[PDB]
Length: 174
Image (cartoon, rainbow, N blue to C red; front, side, top):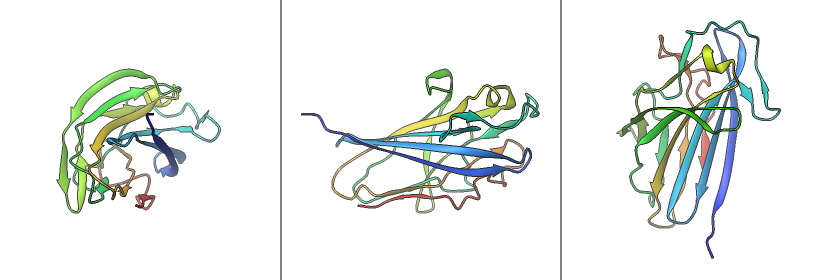
């Protein structure tokens, strides 16, 4: 008898340049041995599956989905171990991988973790309904599997303007 539990979190912010919604999705699966995290930033509204406005973003515009050490992405409860590397890739509308980027190194900053700059997405993809996706695992060693995740998106120049604020924290207790 294998058992697992999955939560999907979604939220929304504002791209300052194009004045459009920008969205994130975070899927977290707990199978008893580890938490698997999948984090996607996209212009496709997860509620409707409709792509945002309006064709008028240039192809070489580009965004990151992780801050560097401008901000902590992830904090972990007492019975979660060290996160793996963070795989980075572009996903299509159905979440299947289109191409892959360098795997990032998860490091500690502050009370939690970040990974640093690695992948980006450019209008040439955002406009196809694609997302910029990162995934990693964290071992479970006991009962306190709480965590918080803070989403991030910014154009590759000007790393300081997080499109999500970033006051849109995901907080899971235990």
